[PDB]
Image (cartoon, helix red, strand yellow):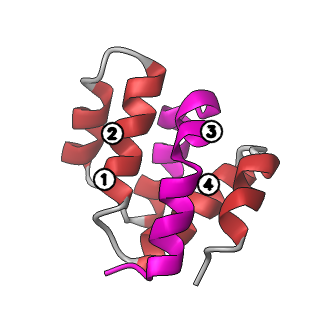
Amino acid sequence: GMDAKARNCLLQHREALEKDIKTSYIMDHMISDGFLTISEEEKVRNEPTQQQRAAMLIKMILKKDNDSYVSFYNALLHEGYKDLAALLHDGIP
């Protein structure tokens, strides 16, 4: 569903993302945008640590469409993760 460029960007920067991001905030945006289901939210929330939640959310997004990548970018950007957003800018469709 997603462009290779986007996929690879995510795969390249996932460790950096997994490290810093507060997943619940990003998810709230993505749920608002309608690219993330309550069931998916819960599955992420079921992960014990923030890094494990982040990893799960990214694993999920890698199985979604271009729109979802952008939603993720927008979320990061609106939550002030400007550095991490920049890393994914090059891969945006």
**Toward the viewer: 12 or 33?**
12
**Toward the viewer: 28 or 13?**
13
Which residue occupies the extreme top position in the image?
48
Q: Secondary structure at mark 4?
A: helix
Give the magenta part as a residue range: 1-29
Amino acid carrying mark 3 in the image:
Ala
Which of marks 2 and 3 precedes in the sequence?
Answer: 3
**Residue wearing tag 3:** 16
Q: Secondary structure at mark 3?
A: helix
C-alpha gap between disc 3 and disc 2: 14 Å
Q: Nearer the viewer, mark 4 or mark 1?
A: 1
Asked if labels 1 and 2 touch by Cβ distance under 8 angstroms, the answer is yes
Which of marks 4 and 3 precedes in the sequence?
Answer: 3
**Residue wearing tag 4:** 75
Q: Residues within 10 Å of mark 1 (few under 14, many from 20)?
A: some
Which of marks 2 and 4 precedes in the sequence?
Answer: 2
C-alpha gap between disc 3 and disc 4: 16 Å
Residue at 80% in and 50% down: 82
Amino acid carrying mark 2 in the image:
Met
Q: Residues within 10 Å of mark 2 (few under 14, many from 20)?
A: many
C-alpha gap between disc 2 and disc 1: 6 Å
Amino acid carrying mark 1 in the image:
Met
**Residue wearing tag 1:** 60
Which of marks 3 and 1 precedes in the sequence?
Answer: 3
Using the rendered view, name the quadrant where residue 49 is placed. top left
| Residue 56: assigned label | 2
Secondary structure, magenta segment, majority class = helix
Q: Nearer the viewer, mark 3 or mark 2?
A: 3
In screen coordinates, is 80 left or right of 20?
right
Q: Position of residue 4 (x, y in %)?
A: 44, 79
